[PDB]
Image (cartoon, coloured by chain):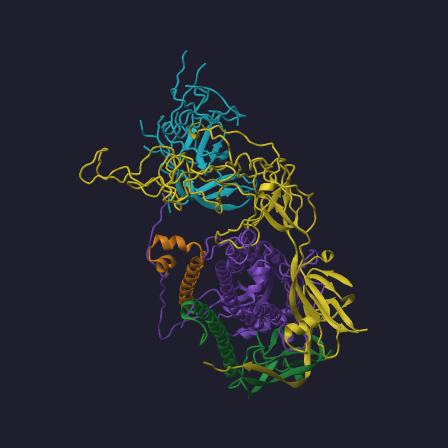
Chain colours: A cyan, B yellow, C purple, D green, E orange
Amino acid sequence: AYTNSFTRGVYYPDKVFRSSVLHSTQDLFLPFFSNVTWFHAIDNPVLPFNDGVYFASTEKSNIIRGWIFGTTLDSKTQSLLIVNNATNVVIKVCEFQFCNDPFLGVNCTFEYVSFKNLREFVFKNIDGYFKIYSKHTPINLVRDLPQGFSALEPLVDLPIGINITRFQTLLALHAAYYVGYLQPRTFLLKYNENGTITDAVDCALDP
Amino acid sequence: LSETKCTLKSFTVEKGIYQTSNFRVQPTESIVRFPNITNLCPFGEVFNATRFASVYAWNRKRISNCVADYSVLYNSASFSTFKCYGVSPTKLNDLCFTNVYADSFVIRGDEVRQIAPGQTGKIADYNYKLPDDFTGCVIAWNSNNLDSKVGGNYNYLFRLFRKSNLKPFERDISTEIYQAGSTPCNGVEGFNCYFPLQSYGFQPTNGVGYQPYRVVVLSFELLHAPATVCGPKKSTNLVKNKCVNFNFNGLTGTGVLTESNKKFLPFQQFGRDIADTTDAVRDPQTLEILDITPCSFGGVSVITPGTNTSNQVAVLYQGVNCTEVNVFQTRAGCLIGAEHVNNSYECDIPIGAGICASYQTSQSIIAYTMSLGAENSVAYSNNSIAIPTNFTISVTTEILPVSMTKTS
Amino acid sequence: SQSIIAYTMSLGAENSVAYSNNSIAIPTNFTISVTTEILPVSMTKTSVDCTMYICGDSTECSNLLLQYGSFCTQLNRALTGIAVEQDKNTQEVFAQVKQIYKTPPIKDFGGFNFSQILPDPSKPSKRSPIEDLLFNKVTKFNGLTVLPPLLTDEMIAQYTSALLAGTITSGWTFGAGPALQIPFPMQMAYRFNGIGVTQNVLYENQKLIANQFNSAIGKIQDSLSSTPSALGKLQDVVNQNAQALNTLVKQLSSNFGAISSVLNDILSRLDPPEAEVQIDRLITGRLQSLQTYVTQQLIRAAEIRASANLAATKMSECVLGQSKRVDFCGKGYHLMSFPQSAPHGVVFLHVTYVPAQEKNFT
Amino acid sequence: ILSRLDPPEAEVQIDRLITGRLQSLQTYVTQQLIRAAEIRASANLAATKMSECVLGQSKRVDFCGKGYHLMSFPQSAPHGVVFLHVTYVPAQEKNFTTAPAICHDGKAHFPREGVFVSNGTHWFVTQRNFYEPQIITTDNTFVSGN
Amino acid sequence: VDCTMYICGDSTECSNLLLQYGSFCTQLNRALTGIAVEQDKNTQEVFA
């Protein structure tokens, strides 16, 4: 009922260069080489966020173009819609009380400024600044994730303040995203000679 | 010579070598060389907005590329409190810091001093994914005449007392509830059901903390290998190969900035070494990486014979290159006041690295190399043997301690 | 199919001896063997500045630190004592010879080949091939300093070579008086007579003895080259001091009563006379961390002194002469001894005599 | 700490002094412990030396002085002891040709104790620490082998 | 002897407050185990 992500879910907690050294730290993490959530909702569940959520979308032809992260829809606080044109970020909500989920006819869609392709994301928000992580690797097994090792890095720290718990996304006019709740754990990391993470070890897995 | 006399608390110094003090290369100047973003906008238009777009539809804007007479506001030096414990005092004042946030509220004037986590309301209970990310020493202030009006802004709220436990700084816009209830009154009264409304009173005689403000927005990042963002100041030209006090990206120190070779990935904030000290910093204008090397220092040792007959002395510097301060250079350090000869004797006064000095004839201290002793060889052959014929007697002497005194 | 299993101790094999009132055994053949042991001799030397390490070069720190006393001043003397003691031991152990001797050009020693042990003039460092293997197998500034030793491996090798040349040429005579030459087989006959065997036996088996000795000399080098785990006694001494220094350095990054550690954020943004109860507790805590390290160094040096004394006695007794003490200069009966230098240590080579075969008699 | 200032402000001050005066004792006692610890080993060495070099004669090389040991005498001193060693040393040497063994009548001979030394015209047998020539004779030699 | 439980008596507050000092009790345990190991070395070496 619970697979392993194997070596998935490793990101730089802070960012200070090191070389040919071994470092350890404690922070919120998805547990390593453990009872990872093979989502036994049986693969596309919808769940709240709590303290942390890991994300990994299985999208290849951009069947779903725009992620929507609503939280409560209480008409009061906000719902930030960030769709990126690789140059800009939309800061808008589509909230003046029009419908929220549109459909493909073959609910406002305006824009503003700010498996050979694996898009993986970690959505962590730090006292206003939202840490957004990304990567791009190819795979061959069409069914599930591989056992390989990779490193994940963040992109931006945009400072406004907004939470994201209970959301669902779709397109506009004209997946097995494993919700891995972040948990506090102590980890050891391995740095190569070039300042690139190459290995990691969980401490509480086994003696 | 007189320093040794002071250090020995005596008027007669015997033959030998002694240590007096530690010589430190004096820091010459101080340099502040920060990277250039050519703009310092977000202090006047950001901190005090005029119109406040609804938080529910927040419209960010990259407020930058402007210059004004901002020095008027912050030219004052009335910053008093620095109380945030643990850290030792030396070198904060030149930090370019990252994170700042607060709230602006009509807090129920009965509670002025309870701005703390653990409350309800659209801003207090549920807005944001907030960890336990506390880095910095708190900032707060008041402003009445320039911006606000007496009476308050009815937007956001904090508290300390509700019907049950409030939802403590899971300030997470979701409507999750921390449940501490047993039975519902369903909005109607009866047996053991308090009145949900209460009379606190809109009075001017209560606390003043029912008054309006607004808080700030600032964008700064933490990153790994060369970016080009943090510096506000008119920066001097960087002085290479000089032991000066520096100031880069927030942290100061004294040393020499040199050329590096570490190939990198362009998302920097700061670089550090193995021993928790800073290894290398990054170019202010360009994408280059600069190193940091601490300035020199070392102890001072005095070499001299006894003062019974001679007054001349000499000085030794340990572990310092000679060019950085008669002069002679040795692997043990820099030697001053000695003469180098082409001869070998046995040791008189030890120095180090197989070098010994002595007072010899006109008379001065001279340094020479080790000499183990005389050489000998014996004619060996397959049919030779030596035999003694006469003998002698000799007597020696040895000394050994046995005990000492007893006290209580 | 392998797994971890537990078992009960066994003290070894069993043996039985045939005893009677009129029986006796006696050996007939013999053999030669060579052993090896390693000892440490000295220890690294360091120094530390007290005031700069504690205060971090703050006048507002120094002007109140002096209120306390001269404890760090006497700590300097405490360290200086060990600094001198190291060189005392190093000089004393190797300074037992007064004059330098050298090998005759021609190596005619009755079939005994000493190539593996004699120095090689061809190499830039005039060392034996065994010494080369020994060298190969053996592998910030916050007021801490490292001082170079007075003596160097260059003259250490000279002392060892002089010792070997003197003994191989004059036996034990030079250990008490002037050097007297003597043929090598004659000296070996003296040793054999001293062990309690008539000297004609040596004359009747010289060819076999030389072959056995040469074979053992070749064998030992390969054994040492193959087995790398014999130098742990030298390794751990360095490792412990290295680890202790990093522990001391890292102790600077500690909170020590107040809520954090680092050394930057009380003076420049605060009104001046505001942080007594913090800086005083911090300086007291930081100072307290020093005497522990000092005590550890004192204890370790005290043990090292005893080790050095034992090594000096062993060399002075086994090398310069022949020992009658059992199991002192190696297992079995003792004949020869050859020393070799090593980084912060010394290696001895023993030569032993062992009976081989048996036979029953009445 | 005796006669000069009020309790409710001085009790929070005297404690600092009393706690500052104690580590000064602690360090002193540790120092004395270490010094006594090494003095004990020195004393044991001295006792062993006296036992093996005074009451008898020692064969260990370079133990009771330099050279061949003969006798010893002790002397007392404040907080210590002093030894007087007596030694024996040779001082004059010569040398001639030698030989390991002698053949006569087809039978080999070996010296019972000593060496064979020739002056160039005659052969003599002598001990190994003092020179005096003896006539080679069968009472000081034994025969073995061919 | 265990440093943490002996000092704090199994209190979370004491435990987290203790971290503002360092890890000296770790090297205390290291020294204790070091002497404990050497005891067995002596006992084996005398009779072996």
The front one of B41 and E39 is B41
Q: Residue furthest top?
A: A106
Q: In the picture shown, does residue C26 fall above or below A144?
A: below
Q: In the picture shown, does residue D67 fall above or below B232?
A: below
Q: Residue furthest left?
A: B191
Q: Relative to C163, is D43 on the left or the right?
A: left
Total numbered labels = 0
The front one of C221 and C343 is C343
Q: In the picture shown, does residue B16 fall above or below C296?
A: below
The front one of B1 and C351 is B1
In the rendered image, is residue C150 in sight? no
Q: Relative to C200, is C165 on the left or the right?
A: right
Residue drawn at point x = 45 percent, y = 31 percent: A121
Q: Relative to E37, is C41 on the left or the right?
A: right
Q: Quadrant of residue D2?
A: bottom left
Q: In the picture shown, does residue B155 fall above or below D106?
A: above
The front one of B64 and E14 is B64
In the rendered image, is residue A58 in sight? yes
List x then y, in percent, for residue C313: 55, 72
Q: Quadrant of the N terminus of chain B?
A: bottom right
List x then y, in percent, for residue D25: 47, 73
Q: Quadrant of the C terminus of chain B?
A: bottom left
Q: Residue furthest right?
A: B362
List x then y, in percent, for residue C288: 49, 63
List x then y, in percent, for residue E6: 35, 60
